[PDB]
C-alpha cells in the first residue's frame, strides 16, 4: 500500500488554523498539521502548500468597512504570509525541511516565490509553503492553489476544508459526493472554491480533492488512495 | 485661537492595542478618526512620523510561550505592524492626507523600504511618514522603534498614544490602586520603577534627551491638546 | 471644438501585435505615433495607464508547443512586455511626455517595480504609467492584466488597442465572413461566444462593470476619437 | 583522452539560436546545445555560459532608429535574459543542473549575478548562465564573456561563431588560422570580437578559442584538445 | 578532550584586523584568524561571526567632525561589510565554507541576513559572517553580537579583544577576573562592551567570554574549556 | 561678472585620493569645501553628476597583491566609493544642496540604486546626483565609470578632479622632471603615452568624443574656474 500521488498542492484555508475563539492562529492545530505533513514527506510525497489568510483578514471584508479594496487585499495577502510563517515554524520544530516563499517579496522573513527554486526544493523533498497567494488583489488563495498547483505540476490540489467534502448543499438532508466532474459542479452550481480558481483548475485539468483537515488521518487517507472526501476531475 | 503648536516635528507611536477598540483586528472607526486628527496636525504645519504597534494582532513573546521560535514570533509581530501601517496609511489617503508607509523590513510593492534620507525629505515636504516593522530586529518592541526613529528624524518629542490617560502606577484596568503621574523624569521612572516603555527604549530616549509624552488616543482631540501644549497625559523629560 | 473628453482616466492596453507593423520586433514609427497620440490625451487632462502586450516577440503558449516548459515560456512572454514597455516609455520621453515604466516582476534599475499606491499617485500627477509583465503570473495574458490593473487604478474604461477596427465574428484577416459589432454586452459576448479577451479577463471586467472599448490603433487618431466619444470600435458594457 | 580544460566560459552569440527565418529563438538549436553542454558537464568540465541577444535586439540598431542608446542597450541586455531563460530551460529538460544569473536583477525569473555564488555553483558542477552581459550599456556580450571569464578564472573563453574560426578575411581566398597571439590579431586587424573585450582578454591573458558552434562535436573537440577552430593566446 | 561549545557567536572587533599602522585591514591577521576558525569548524563547532568596523569608521567619530550621526553610522555599518568581505575571503582561501550576510541588503556582494538561512548554514557547518551589525544607527557591533548570538541560540558570545580578559581596571596594578556575573560587572562598573549590549546579553542569559584574539591558540583554548580569558554568566 | 558657465551639464569625478587630505580616511574640511563649490554650480544652473573614487580607502589591485581574491578586492573598492559617496552626499545636504546617492550595486536603504532614467530626471530637476560603486564590475576603475556615466547622462564634459594641476609627464610628487600639458588630443595621450585615466576609460571617452578636463580639486575655486571657462588644468579633446 503505497501513496497514490507524488507531488501535491495542499491548500490550507486560513480558518483551519483558528482556535475556539475563531481568530488568530492556534498552536495545537499547526502542530498537528506539521505531524501530518511530516508523514507525507517521509512517504516520499512532494508537498507544496498554499495557505489562506481569512483567519486574520479578508480584503473584501475590509473594503465593506470603507478601506480601499486593493489595500485590503494587500493586508489579506500579508495575513497569508503570517500563517505561512507560523506553519513553516511548526514544520521546522517538527524537524521537517521547509521553505516559505512569498509572491510578494519580503526580504529576510522568507524567500520570494520562484518557480525554478520551488521545483528544485520539491525534488529535494523540501516542503514548499507558498504565501501571498497570487500576489494580486481581487483573487483568493484558492486561485493561487490552482495556479501554483498547475505551475509545479502537482498531481492534485487537496483543498482542506472543515467538511468531509462536497455536499448537495451545505450540510440537514445534504449528502456527500465521492466524485464529480467540473461540468457537474458548475451544472448543479455546487460549492467548490471560487469560480476563477475552479475554472482555472478545469481549463488545465487539475484534479481537485475536497477533504476534511480536522479529521485526523484524512490527509494520509487521501494520499493513500483511500475513500475520503470528494474527487473532482474530468 | 491665537495659540500655536509647541512642536514642529513629532514621532507619534500608535500602539496596536489602541487600534483594537473592542472585538481582535482593527477598528475602522478609530483609524478614520486618527486620520482626521493627524490631518489637522499636518495642516498645522507639524511634520509627523508615525511608529505603529502590532500587539493588536501578534506579540512575538506571546507566540513563543505557545511554543513557536521567538524569532519567527517577532517576525510575525513585525509583519503585524506592517498590516496596521497599511490600514493607517489608507485611512490617511482616504482623508486626503499625503502619506508614505516605510517598513524596516523590505516588502517592496506593498510599501516603501524605510530610508532615513527619504524619511527626512518626506517630513520636510509635509508627508506623514509611517514607520512599520519597528526596528526590524526581534527581541525589541515598537516602543524601541519609536525612540530610535524619533532620534533618527530628530523629532522634538515622542508621543506615546495608548489606551490610558498616562503613565500609571499599575495597569488601571486590573489594579484599582492604579494612579498616574502628570510629570516624571527619566530618573523618577527608574526609582519609581514606573512603566512607560521597555527599559531598552527609555534608556535610548534618555541618553539623547528625547522627551516623551504619554497620552490616551481613545480620547478624541487629545493628540491636538498635546500638540497645542495643553494639559494631557504624562510628560517625561530630563 | 467645444467638445471635451468623455473619460478622465483610462487603461490603454497596447497589444504587441499592433507594435509589429510589418517585418518581428518593434516598429519605431508606430511607437513614435502612439507617443504623440498619448501626448495629446495627457494634455487633455486624461490620466493614462498603459498595459502593453508582448506577443510581437514571445507567446508562452507558442513556446510551450515547441517543447519549452510553459512557465518559462510565459516568463519570457512577460519579459517581452517589459521590452515593449521600455521602447514605449522611451518614445514617450522623446516626445516630452512624463512617463514611468512599472513591472509586475521587479527588474529594478531598468524600471520601477509596479506599485498600486505609486501608480495612483503618478496618474494623479499626470504621468503616463506603463504596466509591464502583465499580471506577473504565468497562464495569463496581458488582457487579464489590462482588466486587473484597470480595476485597480479605477479607470473609467479599458481601451483595447488592436489591429482590427473592433470585435469581429472571426479573425478578419483569415475569414472573409468576418463582421464586427459596434455594441455588445458582457452577456452577448458570451452567447455569441465572441472574441474580445480571454474569458478570465472578460469575466473580471464584467463582475466589476469595467466597460471595454476595442478599437484599431493602426488608425491614426482613433484613440483620440474614442476619448472624445466619437464612433470608433466596439463598446462592451453591461 | 581526457579533456584539456577544467572550467570554461562558453560564449554563445545570439544569432546562433536563430532559426531559418533569422529571428527569435529556434528550439532545435537550443535542444542540441543542451546535449553538447550536457556532455561537457559529464566530462567533469565546469561551464559558465555568457549568452548574446543580437538575435532579438541590438541597442546600437535601436538607436539608429531613433531610440535613446541607453534604453536600446537595456532592451538588448533584456534580450540576453530571454535567451538565457530559453537556454536554461533546454538544459533542465535535458536533465542538466543549471542556474541562470543576471547582471540586472530580475527577481523570480532568475537570480542576480553573484561571483561567490557563481564559483560555488561551478564547483558543484552546475552550468551557470550569465545574462545581461556586463549590466552596462555601450558594451557587448563579448566584453561580458571576457569579464566573467576572468572573474570565474575560466581556463579559456570559447567564442562560438557560425564560422570554423579566425580567417585572414571574412571567408573566397581567406584561410583559417589555427593559432594567434593578441599582438598578431591587432597587428593584422583580424576580426575577433569587439576591441574593448579583446583588449580586456589580452591584459589578463585570458586565452580565446574561436570555433564553429554549428559543427556538431566541435565544442567537444575544443575541450578535448583536438584540432578545431583558432586559439588566441600570448 | 572535546570542545565545550557547539555553536558560538564570535565577535571580532574591527581594530583586531589592523596592521601596525593602526588602520585599514592587515592580511596576515585575517589569514591567521581563518586558520583558527578553520580549526573550530573541523572540531565540529558551529561558528557565527559578528565583525566590527571601527578600524575604518566610527559613526560617533564622524559625527563629532560634523557629519549627520545617522550617515556616520551607515558608513560604520558599511565598514563592517568591508571587514566581513575580507574575512570571508580569508576563509575561502583557507578552504573554509563561509557565507557573508548583511543586515543591510547589498545584492551581489554578499547575502542579506536571514535568520532561517543562518541557522540552516550553521547546521551545515558553514561559517556565517554577520555584517552591518544590527542594521540600525546608534548601536555597536557588540549589540549585534549579543542580538545575533541570542537569535542563533549560540552557547556563548566570544568577545575577542586585544587584552587577556576583564581587568579590575585597564591594565599597572589591575588584575584579571576569571569569572564574573552580570551583576558584579555592573556593580563594579567593569568595562565589558556597551551597556545596551551587555544588558541585552544579561536579560537573555547569554554568557560572554572575553579573551585575547592576539594570543595564538586562545580561541581554541576557550572552546576547549581551558583556562583562558574571563567568563561572564549568572 | 557678466560671464556665464561654459557647460550646462558635467560629470565631476572626485578621486578618492583628493578626499584624503593628510592623515587614511576622509578629510571633513575638504568635503565641506567641495559641497560649497558644487553648491555654487547648482545655483549657476549647472546640472551635476558626480562619480566618486574610493582609493583613499581600498584599491582592489592593492588588496590582491596582499593575497586577496581580486574580485573581492574590487568589491571592497567599490564599497569604499559608496562610503565616500555617503560622506559627500551628507556634506551636500548639510550645505543645503539637494542631492541623491545612487549605487551601481544596490544597497537599498542607505542609498538609491543607480537608474539612468531616474538620474536624468534628477539632473533636470537640479539635483546633484552622486554615482557610486563605479561601473559595478571588478577589473575597472572609477575613471571608467566617470566616462561611462558621463556618456550615459550626456554630460558636456568629464571633469577629473585630482591632486595635481593637470596631466603631467610623470607623477609630480615622485619625479622632479614632471611637467604637465595644458592641451592634448586623445591621440597625443596615446603617442605621448601620457597618463590621464586607464586606457579602457579614455578609449570610451574618445569613441564618443567626450571631452575631458583634468584639474586640481585641492585648489579652492578651481572647479568654478573650469566651469566659467578660465585657464585651469589640462583639456583633452579630439
Ligand atoms: O492572490 C490572492 C490571494 C488572496 N488575496 C487576499 O488575501 C486574503 C486571503 O484570504 P483567503 O484567500 O484565505 O480568503 C483574501 O481574502 C484576499 O483579500 C488576494 O488579494 N489575492
Ligand atoms: O523592533 C521590533 C518591533 C516589534 N517586534 C515584534 O512585533 C510586535 C509589535 O507589536 P508591539 O507589541 O510593539 O505593538 C512585538 O510584540 C514583537 O514581537 C519586533 O520583533 N521588533
Ligand atoms: O499576466 C501575464 C501576461 C502575459 N504573460 C505571457 O507573456 C505574453 C504577453 O504577450 P500577450 O500575448 O499578452 O501580448 C503572453 O503570451 C504570455 O505567455 C503571462 O505569462 N502572464
Ligand atoms: O554588457 C552588455 C552586453 C550587451 N549589451 C546590449 O545588449 C545587446 C546584446 O547583444 P550582443 O552582445 O549579443 O550583440 C547588445 O547589442 C547591446 O545593445 C549592453 O548594452 N551591455
Ligand atoms: O548595529 C550597529 C553596529 C555598528 N554601527 C556603526 O558602525 C560602526 C561599527 O564599528 P564598531 O561597532 O566595530 O565600533 C560603529 O562605530 C557605528 O558607527 C551602527 O550604527 N549600528
Ligand atoms: O567600476 C569599478 C570602479 C571601481 N572598482 C574598485 O574600487 C576601487 C575604487 O577606487 P578608485 O581607484 O576608482 O578611486 C578601485 O581601486 C577598484 O578596486 C571596481 O572594481 N570597479
Image (tube, coloured by chain):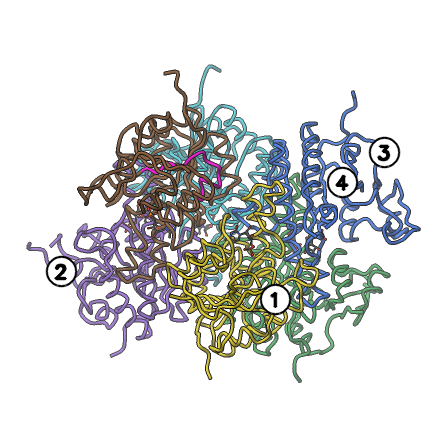
Chain colours: A green, B cyan, C blue, D yellow, E purple, F brown
Q: Chain of mark 2?
A: E
- In this figure, which residue is indicated by the disc labeled 4? C159
Which quadrant: the C terminus of chain B? top left
Which residue lies under the disc numbered 3? C231
Image location (x, y in percent) of residue E83: 31, 55
Q: Residue at x 67, y 46 (%)?
A: A61
Q: How many marks?
A: 4
Query: x and y percent of residue E121 in the render?
Result: 41, 67
Residue E176's mark?
Answer: 2
Q: Which residue is mark 1?
A: D89
Distance between the alpha carbons at the discs numbered 3 and 1:
47 Å
Residue E234 in view of the camera: no
* Direction from residue F190 to residue A9 in the image, left or right: right
In this orientation, does residue B49 appear? yes
Residue A110 placement, left or right of E124:
right
Kind of element beneath mark 3:
loop
The mark closer to the camera, 2 or 3, is 3
The residues tagged by marks 4 and 1 sit, at their Cα atoms, a distance apart of: 35 Å
- Subunit bearing disc 1: D
- Quadrant housing residue D148: bottom left
Q: Is residue D229 above or below residue A148?
A: below
Q: Is mark 1 within 8 Å of ligand 3?
A: no
Amino acid at each position: 500500500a503505497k501513496p497514490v500521488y507524488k507531488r501535491i498542492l495542499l491548500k490550507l484555508s486560513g480558518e483551519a488554523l483558528q482556535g475556539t475563539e475563531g481568530f488568530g492562529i492556534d498552536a495545537s492545530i499547526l502542530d498537528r498539521m506539521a505531524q501530518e505533513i511530516k508523514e507525507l514527506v517521509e512517504l516520499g510525497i512532494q508537498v507544496g502548500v498554499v495557505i489562506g489568510g481569512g483567519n486574520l483578514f479578508r480584503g473584501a471584508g475590509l473594503a465593506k468597512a470603507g478601506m480601499n479594496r486593493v489595500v485590503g487585499d494587500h493586508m489579506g495577502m500579508l495575513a497569508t504570509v503570517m500563517n505561512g510563517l507560523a506553519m513553516r515554524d511548526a514544520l521546522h520544530r517538527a524537524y521537517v525541511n521547509a521553505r516559505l516563499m512569498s509572491a510578494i517579496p519580503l526580504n529576510g522573513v522568507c524567500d520570494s516565490y520562484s518557480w525554478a527554486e520551488a521545483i528544485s526544493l520539491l525534488r529535494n523533498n523540501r516542503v514548499v509553503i507558498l504565501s501571498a497567494g497570487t500576489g494580486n488583489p481581487f483573487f483568493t488563495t484558492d486561485s493561487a492553489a490552482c495556479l501554483r498547483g498547475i505551475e509545479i505540476e502537482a498531481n492534485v490540489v487537496l483543498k482542506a476544508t472543515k467538511v468531509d467534502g462536497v455536499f448537495t448543499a451545505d450540510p440537514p438532508t445534504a449528502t456527500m459526493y465521492e466524485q464529480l466532474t467540473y461540468s457537474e459542479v458548475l451544472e448543479k452550481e455546487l460549492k467548490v472554491m471560487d469560480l476563477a480558481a475552479f475554472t482555472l483548475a478545469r481549463d488545465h485539468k487539475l484534479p481537485i480533492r475536497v477533504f476534511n483537515m480536522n479529521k485526523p488521518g484524512a490527509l494520509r487517507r487521501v494520499v493513500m488512495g483511500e475513500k475520503e472526501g470528494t474527487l473532482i476531475t474530468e
